[PDB]
Amino acid sequence: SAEDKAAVERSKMIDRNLREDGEKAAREVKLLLLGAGESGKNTIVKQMKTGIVETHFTFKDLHFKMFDVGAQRSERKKWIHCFEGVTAIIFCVALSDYDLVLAEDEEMNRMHESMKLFDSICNNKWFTDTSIILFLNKKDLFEEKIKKSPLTICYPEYAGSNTYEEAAAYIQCQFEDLNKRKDTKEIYTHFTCSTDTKNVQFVFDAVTDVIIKNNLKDCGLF
Amino acid sequence: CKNFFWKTFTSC
Amino acid sequence: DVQLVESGGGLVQPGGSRKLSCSASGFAFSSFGMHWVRQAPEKGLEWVAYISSGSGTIYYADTVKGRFTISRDDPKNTLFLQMTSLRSEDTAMYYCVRSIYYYGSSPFDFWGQGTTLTVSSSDIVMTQATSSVPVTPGESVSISCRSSKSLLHSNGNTYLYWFLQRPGQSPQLLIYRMSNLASGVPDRFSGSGSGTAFTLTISRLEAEDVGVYYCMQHLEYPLTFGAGTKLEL
Amino acid sequence: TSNAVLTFIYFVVCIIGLCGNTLVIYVILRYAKMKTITNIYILNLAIADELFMLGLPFLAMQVALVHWPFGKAICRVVMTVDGINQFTSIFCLTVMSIDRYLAVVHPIKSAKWRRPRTAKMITMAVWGVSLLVILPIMIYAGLRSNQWGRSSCTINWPGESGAWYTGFIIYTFILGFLVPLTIICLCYLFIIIKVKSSGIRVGSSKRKKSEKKVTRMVSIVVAVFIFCWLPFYIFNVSSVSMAISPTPALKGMFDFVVVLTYANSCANPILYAFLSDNFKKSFQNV
Amino acid sequence: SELDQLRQEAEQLKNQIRDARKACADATLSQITNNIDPVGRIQMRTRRTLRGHLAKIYAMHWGTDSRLLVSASQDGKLIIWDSYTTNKVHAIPLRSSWVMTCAYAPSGNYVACGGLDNICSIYNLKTREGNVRVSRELAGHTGYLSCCRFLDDNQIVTSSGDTTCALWDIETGQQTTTFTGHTGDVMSLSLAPDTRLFVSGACDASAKLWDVREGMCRQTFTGHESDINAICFFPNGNAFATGSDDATCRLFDLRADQELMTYSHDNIICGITSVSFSKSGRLLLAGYDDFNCNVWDALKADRAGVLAGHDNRVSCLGVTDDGMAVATGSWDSFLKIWNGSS
Amino acid sequence: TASIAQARKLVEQLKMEANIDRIKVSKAAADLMAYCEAHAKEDPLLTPVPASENPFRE
């Protein structure tokens, strides 16, 4: 018909804008920002600028969408498959919680409460091949606090030495042993610093390496 | 006899 | 309001050339197909040209094909009509009509104010055998119109349109696809028909229902109007 | 006696060739991920290699009884439909290694140049240049049949024109062997560079023995390419190199090296799909 | 004291309902329908395949004209489809890409959608301009939105993952009613065929019957071992069928207050993402996440059909108002329109 | 005493949960199978309409 063949060519102007916007969206980098609460999750989005809070910080010709989900007080198992195809997961853990306990019901000492959540996110079935860019936030704010009290209040089977650069090695390995999927994905670990460029350059360096190993697996090279 | 050409063994 | 106002032309020698320009305002111009419909003085409407949304389909009337060309620029919301070799049958008031086509839409709903052009010195026939009806308020009128080819289609709808040109004004759409009332049209008007013969029924006439009532088809191009039915008061 | 043992291998190469290669034609046409750049190229390198395997039994009848049972226009088209599918099965092979270059070496600056719209312009242009290279074989398809009566399928020339076997036959090296080799062996030498560069220096990983475990899956791609295509190519240059009398070693191995040159199009389904994990879960799952 | 004997009267008043459900349970619906014949093997074929979504489809809803349908996906697009001719009528770009639900107004003028941004946006489909614009955005929920459903062009009821349902007024933009009985995240809604009641099932394995005018829970239906993911009303309006992560579907009755049937099989172990009935109430369609829909004989509890056309989790499904078709959207980005063949 | 009213409101909901009285199941079960008999042949997915009336023709 005359008016049904104009309904058809409107419909493939719908189609060539769906195809055009869905190929400008497969080029941008999506990132979950998870954490445990006040574990430095605001100073990373301060370095890159009531449900999802999406943040866009295009850095070196690479559009970065970062979805903060920390204001979702619901069951996480019901909405986390929405982030199934996501490029990476930026996880924040405050290093200055290795002594202070959770004030709910005298619970675990707030780094095991982070280890509750790193194990649940890393070994999840939707994140069986999604690399994790793990951040250890308050590096200087516990280095003065590790000189007073050793790293024994949380993990009692520590070797010892009561100082920084073994606590920066034992804690980092204490998160990277929870990765029970080691051939599929990688954990990248960083220590959050006062330099305003070195913390977003690590996200750019570590997410380029997710793109490489995705382009090697999409071909036959992996 | 051109024993070596493209994809044939022509004439010999 | 939605606004189509067209300019350009008014006096041209025969054999000359004029560019018409309809400038759209207050709607999403890029989504509408646009027509030009002209009206010879003390005569009826006839269809000129058409461009689809996206400008990927152009039609013309067989009277003006080769001479006229229609174009749009969507970043400026402007409709054009470049006219060459202007004959003396081209003297008419030219209207600018918007038209959108999806499932259930209302094409030919908003018409422009009309620019005038004065030049100095097969398909479906739509017939309205009545040209004028004497009428007083309170009457129920049933204006009929007839088509040569059947306007019903296999997909199930009958592509007959109804229009009303109040005196001194622009035409407004009353009925699209033989039975559906347009937006802003009072419920008094009602369209019906079957295939080849159609009738438009007004329930009670007011002081605003007086004008010329045209019937147009949209089954295939060219879009042929009828000679309208005047309702004098 | 000697021709009979390799007349069968002209068929069983084409038997496993036409079988595994149209399996890869099935899955991209049917299953998911038809709109990606790896599958639009491995479809076009599978059409080009399944329409390459059909010209093999027309050479198998010529191998044992040396006479073509055709020759009006059938022996002229089997030197063209097998002609185009030679220079488009190893031109769709050198553009699938350009695709793997821009996906891995330039992952950011070339994300906007790898859409599935510029893929269709390349794959149409891949088949277009393939006519513009074989076009001497499309023109000169004459049959030399004067040696006491034997219908051949060979290529003629203006007069005799001995520059056909020195000239044209090395024209198909500077566009048939060397240029698809100096791109495939050059693109993959930068993937091994870019894999060792990113995972070590700037994005600090510890899984870095994959940089040697990507070489062992990519040195094999160029290993089958010389082994299929230049025992054959050193034989056709050897026409000028003191052409000798035919014997079951000369007339046997020469029918074997052009039997070997179709084994590249039997590896291309298994070295680009059946060793990739996105066909090991798309096709091999069902 | 006082801390214990209201806790024990909540024990007593929950004993007050259970044997009162048992006394009204003299026979089973299986035994009363033991004489009827089965429906046979229901064979349906993919008539249309609606394609153009580029991510997982999360919800779809038909129009009441049985021809137009809206579908929601997480590529950020809401698409109104012509189901007859497979072509697009509108494509609506959304503010948040995290859309978990979509709804069609019964008049056709409006389309709602919501999700993880905790609002239900309303869209005007029929404007004097040629586009589709946002009429209102209904903020006021604290959790994600699971289900939006129109009552008419001015009233919409939503569900949310803050354990609350709400009735809104789209003109003013604020909740006229709040429905607070659930203790887990509410996952779906289903309006009655007279829109004086609705049912919502939640992640506390219970479904609650609500009054729209009063704002109070009439009945609370237990019987599931896990989260209720899908609620649909039976066409009578006197029954409703649920679907859980329990790999089971249960049919409840309002006037008998308890569970009649249980639609399960030995080999099925995965959840149920969608539940719908046919126009008779004879078939029960259910979308699973082992990638196929399963037509259930709603009276005999026999799997009398399979719709096996999807490559991923069957995420949403609906039947038209005349029962002529059934669409199934899914995570493989396609809606398929199915129809029984004569 | 915030939890005092919380348990108080919890049994004020269970006031009218139990106060409603229900028909027996055998009356109700024979009602939504009697609905399927009145609307049996106007269900096109159950009993398919002939293909000249089907709006979805391949």
Image: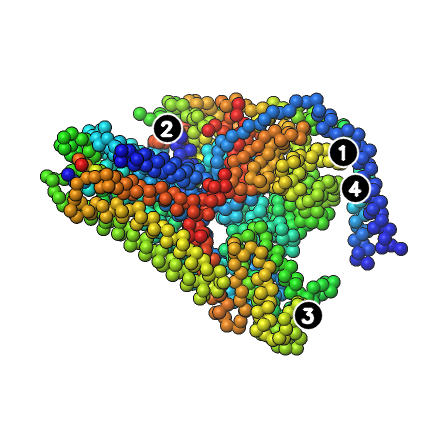
Mark nearest the camera among 4 and 3 is 3
Q: Which of the two residues, C124 or E46, is positioned nearer the viewer here? A: E46
Q: Which mark is residue F17?
A: 4
Whether residue E328 sits left or right of residue E182 in the image: it is left
Which residue is under mark 3? A153
Q: Position of residue C126 (x, y in %)?
A: 37, 26
Q: Residue at x 27, y 33 (%)?
A: D1
- C-alpha gap between disc 4 and disc 3: 51 Å
Instruction: Return the chain for callout 4.
Output: F
Whether residue A202 sits left or right of residue A101 in the image: it is left
Up the image or down, A19 lies above or below E3; here it is: above
Dots 1, 2 in contact, CB < 8 A? no
- C-alpha gap between disc 1 and disc 3: 58 Å
Q: Residue at x 47, y 57 (%)?
A: A210
SS assignment at label 3:
loop
Whether residue C152 sits left or right of residue E120 in the image: it is left
Q: Quadrant of residue E321?
A: top right
- C-alpha gap between disc 4 and disc 2: 72 Å
Q: Taking the image as drawn, is residue E289 in sight?
A: yes
Q: Position of residue D234 (x, y in %)?
A: 23, 48
Q: Position of residue F4 (x, y in %)?
A: 82, 55
Task: Name the amino acid, label 1.
Answer: Ala
Which residue is under mark 2? C227
Up the image or down, E117 lies above or below C46; here it is: below
